[PDB]
Every structure is written in structure tokens, then in C-alpha cells.
Length: 203
Length: 204
Ligand SMILES: [K+]
Ligand SMILES: [Mg+2]
Ligand SMILES: [Zn+2]
Ligand SMILES: [Zn+2]
Image 1 (cartoon, chains in turn brown, green):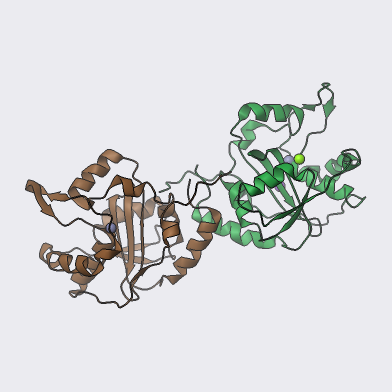
Image 2: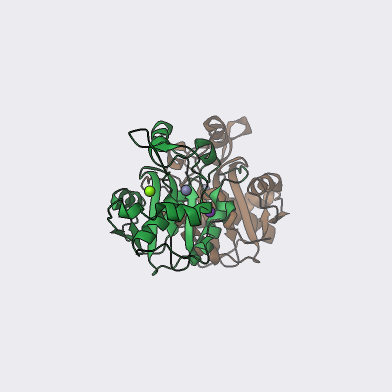
């Protein structure tokens, strides 16, 4: 099951709040073929798209949880199915998205037949992200409270979890070399659309 | 596989513009409200209509229907676009007034889609006078649906003309006006792109 007709109508309208030409960050958690958290962020206006997805492969999700995003499988079951394909399907034509690790984002977009969406790959030096990582989580951490489980670096060293949304803001900071301060930052997607509503008959 | 893609839904929205919300409109179906296999929404004044198909969950009961009413081939329904029934109904104009022969199943069908706003006019009829135009309709407008290949018989094993959702809309329209419609133009707003499933796509 995916988005109902009405939910798709809603999404269509909300996506109008996206500037087709504005510089836009995109980041995902989970593999390209089985994402669990998607973030699309426009720093110029502070508008972003942040939502979740239930992973097919749960074994790989726990590994990625222990090694990367530290997300709980319990929080993702209530996620609205099909949302990932609808959002990417709803993106403006020929949009240029900035990202880190374009390889997987390219596959994700290609799987959705969005070969029109070009990608600017922007890689962050460890020290550049090291500097802004803490600062972004403090200011904007209230936006995502899904990364509760502890994450571990090599040698069993605890580190800060990776959030699709925080990643975007951190990437924006480090590439622009300054913490971006936008008075208003908000998710265009309502809670009603990010998470499952009541089960409905589909014919 | 799952249902309509985003682009499809965007297309359906535009094509539904062809439907006049305030025009008299017929609706009929084949299969039960909980497991329909043919849907027809018909506007006689302009010949604009919505005609599409669906694959049944219950194949066994579908064969009983194929024997006794609509005579549709299960092979022809495999290639039908899934989720289309829910999409078309969700795309119908608000508070639209529909007419039908036996509003029972239609109510439950529309109710199961939270479309209680849509009103149903139960055009009850003789089922004899309501079918005097049956032969005449299939004659003039039989080319509108060739999904009914199977032989249909009554409980007495005597052959009868198959029941078609689209053709029924036209038959009931005939009986409701005491004359066969002279539809100069006809138009199924749904293209073949939406009626049938396209190439498989990764859906996340
Ligand atoms: K047709
Ligand atoms: Mg009928
Ligand atoms: Zn997050
Ligand atoms: Zn038919």
C-alpha cells in the first residue's frame, strides 16, 4: 500500500513550497534500495522535507543502526508507506540537489526514474564536519528524535548518530564554512502524512 | 503492483476535469462492492464516461459471476492497473450525485472509500422495462466493451446476454428516458496508460 489519492493531492500542494532553482541538500539513512530516513533541505528559505520509511531488510537495519543512524525499528512501523516514491516523484523537473556520497543518491533517484535530477557531490573533511556536528545537533536536534539507540565507531568508540536532516544542515554549514542561521525552519510534510493513518480499504 | 504511481495520480487528476460534477451521471459495477471487477461511470449528456477494470481477490466467486452475469475472462483482468478503483473514486468531484440500478452495493463501495458525500439515486426499475433496450444498446454501442466473451446463462441453463457495467449505464439511461441515447461523441477519460499496469517500478 502507498499514499491514497487525497494524500497525493495534499503532497502535490505542499511540494509547491519547494523552490525548483534554490540550492537543495538531500541525504538519506539506510541503503539506497532500502532507505529508512530521507531529508531534503533548502537553506535559503529553511524549508525541508523530512520523513521515514520501514526497512525491508531488518538485519541490515540493525547493523546500520549500530554503526550509523542508531534508529529504532519500533518508531518506523508507523511510517506512511510509499511516501519515499511519491516525494521523489513530486520533485520539480531537472532539479539540482546537493549531497554527500552521490553514488547512492544517484541510484535512489534512478530507481524512481528521475535521471533528470542532477547531483552536486560535496565531500566534507572530517575536521569540517567535526566542528559543526555538535553545533547543529544543539540548535536543530529537536527536529528529529528518532536516533535514540547508541552508535559505535570502530574500536567500540561511541559517536554522534547520523541523521538525514542533521546531515543536510551540517553539510550546508561545512561547505558554506559557517553555521547557517535561519529564523524559521520547518517540515512541509505534516505529521498526518509522515505517519500512518487508520487502515483503509483499497481497491 | 501496489497501486498508482505519483505521475499516474497527477494524470488522473487532470483527466477528471472532463467529468461534469453537476451533470446527471450513471454508475454501475460488476462483481460485489467488496470485490469489483468492472466499473462504469457514465455522463449521457456529453458522452463522457469512466470505464476501467480490476482483478478479483475471490477468483471462485468471480467464476460464478462469469457464469451467471458478466462473463468476464480472468486473463483479461490480470493486466489491470491496481489501486485504480480507489483512485478514481477518490478523484470524483465532491458531493456528486450519481444514479444506479441497485444502490445497495454502490453505497457500500463508496462508503468503503469514505465518500459519503457522493449521493446515490436508486433508479429502481422493472428489470424487464429496464432491459427492453438491452438488445438495442449492445447493437449501437456494443463496441465500447468487448471484455464479456464468456457464455452467460440463467439458473435454467438458458443463454442470456452478458452484463456490462458500461453497457448497463447506457441501458438504464435508455429506460430512464424511454429512448436509446443518440450519443454523437463518446469518451473514456481514462487512457490505456491508466486502465492497465505499466512496466514494473521500484516503490519505496
Ligand atoms: K473503452
Ligand atoms: Mg451491473
Ligand atoms: Zn533523523
Ligand atoms: Zn463491459
